[PDB]
Image (cartoon, coloured by chain):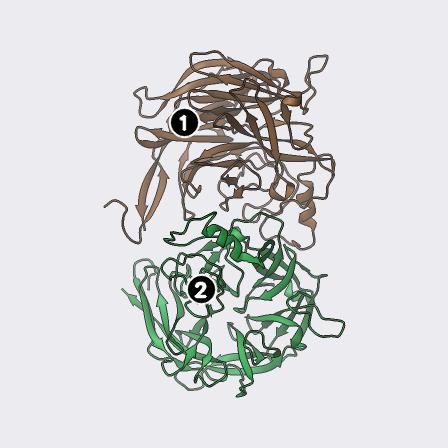
Chain colours: A green, B brown
Amino acid sequence: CNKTNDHFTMQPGVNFYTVPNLGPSSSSADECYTNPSFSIGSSIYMFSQEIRKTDCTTGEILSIQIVLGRIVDKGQQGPQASPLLVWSVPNPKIINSCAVAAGDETGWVLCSVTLTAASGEPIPHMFDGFWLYKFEPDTEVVAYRITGFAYLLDKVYDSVFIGKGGGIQRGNDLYFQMFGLSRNRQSIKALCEHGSCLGTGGGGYQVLCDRAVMSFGSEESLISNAYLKVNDVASGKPTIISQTFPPSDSYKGSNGRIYTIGERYGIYLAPSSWNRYLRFGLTPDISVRSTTWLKEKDPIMKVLTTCTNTDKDMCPEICNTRGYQDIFPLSEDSSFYTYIGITPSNEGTKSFVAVKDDAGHVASITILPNYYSITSATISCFMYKEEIWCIAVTEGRKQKENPQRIYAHSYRVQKMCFH
Amino acid sequence: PGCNKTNDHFTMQPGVNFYTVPNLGPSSSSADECYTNPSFSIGSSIYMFSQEIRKTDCTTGEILSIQIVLGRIVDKGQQGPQASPLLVWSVPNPKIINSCAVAAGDETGWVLCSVTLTAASGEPIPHMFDGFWLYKFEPDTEVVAYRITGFAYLLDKVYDSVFIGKGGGIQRGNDLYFQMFGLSRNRQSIKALCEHGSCLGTGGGGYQVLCDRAVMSFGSEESLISNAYLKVNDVASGKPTIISQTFPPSDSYKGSNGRIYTIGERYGIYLAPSSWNRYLRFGLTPDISVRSTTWLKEKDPIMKVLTTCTNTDKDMCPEICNTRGYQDIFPLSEDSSFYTYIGITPSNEGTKSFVAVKDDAGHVASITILPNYYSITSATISCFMYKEEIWCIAVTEGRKQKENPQRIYAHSYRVQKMCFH
């Protein structure tokens, strides 16, 4: 189909098939499965999950399970998951966060660690560098510790977390996103994009904007986002450099994702503050200056938020948002993308899946109607049986009584040529 | 339908014509005289034009004459806007002038020059500082001269040379603002701006050492080629004073000619590539302050001309090199999200150039200009409202014919509003 003259429609199919056994999962009520990462490669997929005790946010990290596997036909209607290796991150109590990336037959887990006490116990919310784990079918896991000998951040970070969305490989480099506390001696003017907001008073919402990026109310400590580059992975001596987004080009730092989009890249930034619209940029090279942000507002995070602002004007305020609902671009310009929306109910949440075009037409389909709640979504698509398919990995509870768990469902995107 | 609609984008473009603005400034045919370092400023009803006439060389030549023109932009009945000079005047003692630039206001004009130390022989000690001369120009009135030396100025570093940026400055009330670069005195550890693209070994401080050096002047921590805002205070006093506010090496590259702008009720600064960063250094400021200056993200124009830099336009990896152009911009929106400029690209013969408008979405709309000219090596552009349409004049150094000495050429064009998408 001549991409020049012919026109095209993209739509979510009718079915939302289970992809069981993408990762293992236990039945224990005492445990919560949280902060997944999912990256599909040319032939492999990588998946990470954190198993925490009691609390899904501050609960002790009992374990971080990594899965290397393959997406395959098992005869079933949709694509299925064949796990190749199941592995635990060692010394999980010292981990801040970990994310994954898939290449050809090679996966990566990048983990940011915190300072350990003399006692050996964690010094919470700090930064002792990184662990990079290299995963290859039927080969042993390889471990590269990245301390200050082999990493150079562009600010002084007291905490470093890896964006749960995961990363991408490009030649000999990997690309991930990070967030944490940087140290600032610069005056700030934070990004303050809202709609019709009629509250003047002192600097007003720009003062509120400036304050919502600070940690603990001091411009000396910002919660910041950064591109994280891993160089020279073929050497066995990888290094790590960072490019931090300044407050004028970002909201409060958050979990994010890096995307290969054609020969360029993209970046998702889950809301963490007052501005709960889609924060997705494109960049021909992974750099803060060449990053352009999409004018798309949907998905709008309307869940896991202490925010009280309207989705229509999103007026700034000091509030805390905790979700994750990325997109997967379906065209070179992200002109079409797919996403899951999640809306609060009087009891739980209700979700839809959607493909959206440049023009604001949305083809949505309600999903998981017999689930009690779904609270996150990371989606990765691929070619399978010569059709566009996606897997959406989603936290939630099939039953309210149940502990939080992570599920994978599959769906097709129909590409309709109109010749 | 007019643009009050949906999924539609307002944009701007240069027009099809590039009209000559003849006689904006005087010129001679002398084969051994170069016309260089022009300063152009357009006010409400007046225009200021400064130009250096040098002996043989355009860079290191003597200064046989610095001419000033006070004129008005008028409609003389031709297709585009025209220049009527009101006064042509020569800056006294050009030998000792480090550098001048102009500022236009409303029915009042300003020339600010920095002078160097005058030797006993007479010949100026080069690259030295001996104060400022501010000349006031006013229609149907004579030039008033104001010396600003000694305690009448207070620079915020110890500058061993001061140069007024040739871009020009503005008038805000009873005060005047200019850009200034020169060698200042530093004895402090510096981590200078090192923003580039993909470069091998970025982690490892190499490029940071090259960045740190590319601004060092005494070879190390004694002199830094720095930028500054220069404020002239109380021009109605008759005893105007000059204060400076210097950029730290963490907020600027090597110092260079720049320009101060009025942009609405806010302001702007252009800074020309002098070292390895050959992109756009344009900053926006609500007041004229280093702490309130935000640098645009957009990279065009990109000085590919008059440089010894062999780095790539795409990655701009820090190296030690020299760039000596001036291709500034004129903002066409409050946020400089829109703006017009000129781009110049080298050719094994000379240079090829184009006029362009950048939009709020990255798009560049360009028409090639001066095709029968051999070369065009600089560009300063000032716009204004003429016949209820946005018009700009561009003042460009070059050689229409190769064997001819450099002259200063001026042309007019229009910026049109359009909707697409």
Tell me the kind of residue under disc 2.
Answer: Cys
Residue B274's spot in the image, x, y percent?
A: 60, 36
Residue B346 at least partly seen = no
Identity of the residue furthest to the left in this view: B1
Q: Residue lying farthest right? A: A118
Q: CA distance from mark 2 to mark 1?
A: 55 Å
Q: Is residue B64 above or below residue B11?
A: above
Q: What residue is disc 2 on?
A: A307
Q: Where on the picture, by quarter, is residue A32?
A: bottom right
Where is A99 relative to B125, above or below? below
Number of residues whose C-alpha sits closer than 10 Å to that of mark 1, classed few (under 14), some (14–19) or many (20 or more):
many
Mark 2, secondary structure of its residue = loop
- A317 or B81: nearer the viewer: A317
Locate residue B252, reporting x and y percent.
60, 41
In the image, residue B233 sits, relative to residue B4, either above or below, namely above
Look at mark 1 in the image and give the residue it sits on.
B411
